[PDB]
Image (spheres, coloured by chain):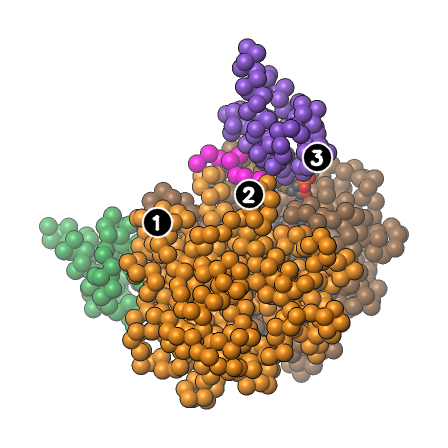
Chain colours: A green, B purple, C brown, D orange
Amino acid sequence: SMGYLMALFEDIQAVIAEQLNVDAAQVTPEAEFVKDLGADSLDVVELIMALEEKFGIEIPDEQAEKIVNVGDVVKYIEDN
Amino acid sequence: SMGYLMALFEDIQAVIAEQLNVDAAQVTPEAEFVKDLGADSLDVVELIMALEEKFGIEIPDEQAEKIVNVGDVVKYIEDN
Amino acid sequence: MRRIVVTGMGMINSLGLNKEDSFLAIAKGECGIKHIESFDASAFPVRIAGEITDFDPTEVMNPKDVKKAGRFIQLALKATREAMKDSGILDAHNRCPEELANRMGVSSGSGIGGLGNIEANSIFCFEKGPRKVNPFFITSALVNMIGGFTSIEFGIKGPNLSSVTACAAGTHAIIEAVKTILLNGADRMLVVGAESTICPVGIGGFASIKALSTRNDEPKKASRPFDKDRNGFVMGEGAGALVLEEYESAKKRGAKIYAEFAGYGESGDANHITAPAPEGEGAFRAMKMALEMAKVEVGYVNAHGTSTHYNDLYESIALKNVFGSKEKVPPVSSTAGQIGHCLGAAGALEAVISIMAMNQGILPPTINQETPDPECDLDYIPNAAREKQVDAVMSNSFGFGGTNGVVIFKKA
Amino acid sequence: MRRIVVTGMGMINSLGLNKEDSFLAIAKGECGIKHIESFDASAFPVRIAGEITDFDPTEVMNPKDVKKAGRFIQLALKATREAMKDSGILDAHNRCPEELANRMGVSSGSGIGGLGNIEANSIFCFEKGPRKVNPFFITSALVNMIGGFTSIEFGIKGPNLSSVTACAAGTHAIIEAVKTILLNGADRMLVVGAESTICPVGIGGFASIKALSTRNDEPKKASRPFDKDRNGFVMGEGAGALVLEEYESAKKRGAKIYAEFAGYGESGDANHITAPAPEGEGAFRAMKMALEMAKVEVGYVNAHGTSTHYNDLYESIALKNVFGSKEKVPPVSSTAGQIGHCLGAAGALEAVISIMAMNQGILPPTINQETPDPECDLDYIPNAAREKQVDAVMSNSFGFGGTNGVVIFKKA
Ligand SMILES: *P(=O)(O)OCC(C)(C)[C@H](O)C(=O)NCCC(=O)NCCS
Ligand SMILES: *P(=O)(O)OCC(C)(C)[C@H](O)C(=O)NCCC(=O)NCCS
Ligand SMILES: *C(=O)CCCCCCCCC
Ligand SMILES: *C(=O)CCCCCCCCC
């Protein structure tokens, strides 16, 4: 399901860019929300919540806590 | 149905007494809400709402303005 | 003691996005009341409101932050941006200069703030659990986030105060800013009243106490202060903002001077939770203290005048009692016919209107005057604006809980 | 300026129904945080709170009226009745004497007021339509209805003011009252901060931003200000009340004198909507201006100390910076461990607590001190009350929106 994984990545990158008012381009796998995307602690929690809704999933609090770069969330949703 | 009428009237009396915190002794059919029961505009509209719920009835607003004594409400409940 | 002047102003309401458009429309007797479209009011007993339909939040704040502010805060940012720019205080980055920042605070007013946001998140929680509560909920809804968001936008770090006295919040926010400056707690204060509560539970809350007009078939004729056929207020949304400044500091800056604060009065009825005191006695006392502090001749009164039976009656009685007789009452108008009664924001909006009326020698009219009310027999500037120069203006505000506030501003 | 004294005090919280029982339990280091019972919190990430389980509203108001007032107003009526009786001012009919009524006002504080009532009526309107919104909804929920109901209950007709600056509201309510007396707008003010937000959307709002402690297994160890294992505040409910009086007026009528008002400070961070300014910069300025204004040696500080990582850290940093070093900071404690953080009510509760600590030479402790936080290196009176006579006490309050208020009271 490589194409499916690619579509999922596209969707996640869209959601992040929309919530942080950033261009999808800036949403790189190695993208730290606070330094590279201009997000803070409030933006982070609401972003994680939009993902859960956009993808009908539930990120447990421990994994959400370790999220530093876009690729962390990307992997989590890949192994979903 | 004398018994039915008595039951409905007793229900109305209990409701009014609970809302205005007045004894069923003072709620005479000729009792006036503002003069005889110590109620104001706000108390009246809240009492009318409770009665509409207590009896699943739906008094129109036009007719509700036309209330002075407990008798008017009881008659309206009778017409039901 | 310390003298305080108005050096910048801004306002947004259902008749304009800034004070020049809005006041012009208000003075011509236009009306911004329309059928509610911001939610589905098809099944409601009241379906009219002073909705602002041409407001775009994206023009006042970054889209990312828009979801972080209740509509009332969005309107406050529009009004305060206009007033701060109007004041000439701001530097090249639209900030308060760093060396003035600690002595410029903010005084905000609102009755309930983000009601629609509490309503929406209350329902999320009830339907799908606390996981569906939006994290931006609290800080989008708290009344004082007006001052929170504005102080951050402008870099102003003085006293950060917020009044929540119901329909008199806008006026109390002015008075608390005046008090702060009088006691040397600040040299400058941004004042802003803001309210936006055109939402199902807000309209429903006022309709269940029968305080709203149900003239749903003619929205532009439903709000009619002092008229015999009035039958309840029409809810408006909006925000007004003022920059207050100690006089010497204003002059030294080269500030423009709209007006000089003259007096205020504050009282409580201690009578009823929604109805006014008999004879508007608490209003009488607030107006009396303001008049005796100001010691000027008031040439125009912007009345609260919400278009309910009780408020217009007892305000007219109190006015007549405080000036001495009917002929001794200055020209009075309520602009709630034009823009609806905007609750918490009303006092702030109506101070801007009152000052502009004085600046321009144009007294805005009380519209929809069709049937004189024998009990309401003052000079309400009926139907059309009155070209008359005045030297001072008084604005009244009263709120649930019997809280009253009055302010007087005099010519510069 | 005019001198001001505290002549009557009252409070109710999760450790007592009056100030005597409550303070004793607080100085004993008892803890009123319990598993939530006022609503079904079984599905919630946070299931603990400072709940009052022994409060009966029908003891402060007649049964017919209980429906008309949110829980925060019921608690406020309880606290103010205690303070008004304690002050000895009430006449034979438990009202303010008429000749004094016009010059006695009320300054009330809350963060959100009747949240549970807005939530309930929002759901009623979202299930059965607007005809199901109770007529008593609005006046049961508005923050200023604290001043509304209390002014009617005691017949006080002076300025009727309400502060809504989030967690700092209770402290700003004191200060607005002081401003009003100083400027001769009143001779006496009833002050009261009251909050009751233990409800689904209230808990969910703070959980969704990760502000609350999730140590649900041990509600008695959850709240631990300045401790290294703090992980969020615990929401508390309650109300505190003071009667303030101009000094000569209190002497003339022979009033009990708990303390004299010494100084206050107010500032805004203009930094962030929830996070504190770096180094507590805003808090530093408010504390310095209260200290510069009181000109007394403070022997005890009741800190805001909500038991969050950022707040307790940045408050400690500001405390050292304002006093000079950690060695120059007076003994400090937060009582939020004992009764939870009571949001808008905290500033009022914590002033009563602080004055009583001074009255009785007993400084209450910051409980649940188990692991020193190297960054929080002050003397927090750990775990056990300290016997020390002080001549002045300082109380800190900060709120969302970066708003800061500080008050200092001195021994009479
Ligand atoms: P009741 O005869 O007290 O009727 C209750 C109402 C809600 C009509 C109340 O008395 C009332 O008129 N309240 C509004 C008073 C007013 O004009 N306030 C200004 C803000 S709407
Ligand atoms: P983010 O890293 O800003 O996280 C937001 C939180 C909710 C942690 C917020 O910054 C916070 O806790 N701020 C200050 C704590 C405080 O002062 N609390 C008393 C009022 S809640
Ligand atoms: C004015 O004093 C009466 C209405 C209170 C204004 C607050 C708006 C809240 C709407 C539910
Ligand atoms: C303190 O500053 C935190 C914000 C308090 C808001 C009032 C409580 C209502 C939220 C459930």
Residue that carries the numbered disc 2 in the rendered image: D67
Q: Residues within 10 Å of mark 3 (few under 14, many from 20)?
A: some
- Residue D132 lies in magenta, yes or no? yes
Q: Name the image quarter holding the C terminus of chain C.
A: bottom right
Q: Amino acid at mark 1?
A: Ala
- Between D163 and A1, the residue placed more toward the observer is D163
Taking the spot 44% from the left edge, 78% from the top edge, the residue there is D386
Is residue C87 shown to the viewer in this render? no
- Per the image, label 1 sits on a secondary structure element best described as loop
Under mark 2, the amino acid is: Lys
Secondary element type, mark 3? helix
Q: What is the chain letter for disc 3?
A: B
**Do the residues marked 1 and 2 share a common chain?**
yes
First of labels 1, 2 by sequence position: 1
Residue C260 x %, y % = 73, 71
**Residue identifier under label 3:** B34
Q: Is residue B5 left or right of residue A50?
A: right
The chain that hosts pointer 1 is D
Which type of secondary structure does the marked residue at label 2 adopt?
loop
Quadrant location of the N terminus of chain C in the rendered image = bottom right
Apparent side of residue D335 relative to residue D296 in the rendered image (left or right) = left
Q: CA distance from mark 2 to mark 3?
A: 19 Å
Task: Tell me which chain the residue with mark 2 is part of.
Answer: D
Q: Nearer the viewer, residue D316 or D208?
A: D316
Q: Mark 3 to mark 1: distance in Å?
A: 42 Å
Is residue D31 visible from the viewing direction of this image?
A: yes
Number of callouts in the render?
Answer: 3
Residue at image mark 1: D41
Residue C9: give x, y in percent of width and height.
64, 65
Q: What is the magenta segment's predominant secondary structure?
A: helix
- What residue span does the magenta drawing correspond to? D127-141
* Residue type highlighted by circle 3: Val
